[PDB]
Image 1 (cartoon, helix red, strand yellow):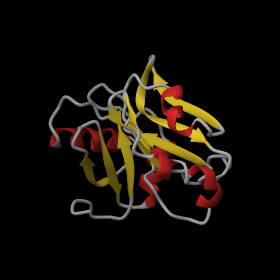
Image 2 (cartoon, one colour):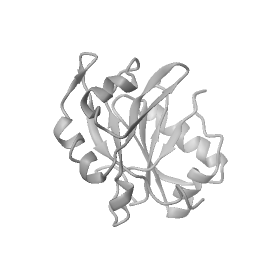
Image 3 (cartoon, helix red, strand yellow):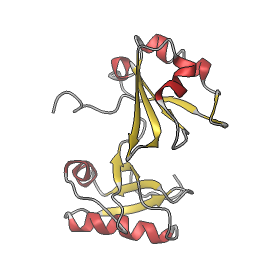
Image 4 (cartoon, helix red, strand yellow):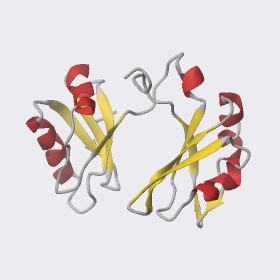
Length: 174
């Protein structure tokens, strides 16, 4: 916390890493202001490539996820939802998420740890990684147990992390 004023916030990314820290918040809240949105407070990470956006109510917050055409400083920001907690996570945990991966990382690479996994799905655009990797295990028990034990491996010289996330509803409903 020690920044946001409301409990309503969303995980944003692709805020361009060229301008200053407080120089990004402006644009972020700007683009939204054009979509009839109102932000109470905006936060930016240390890498100046991602951050969070706080909204007065869940309406404006969820609204941003509905609308489209969000970009600042030329680049197109990415809206997403942070980690949460709910009984739905039971099955939603079937799939694990990977982070701290290089722009040259590959599927087989991360598979070096969860090679026994069921399926692997990397996230790369323009012919380069984005810093993430989604994998669908056979069971949350075999997944959360593999990412919790394998976590700490070394790939491309760096140490890739491991986390779990199934995202909120709407995945199959909508």
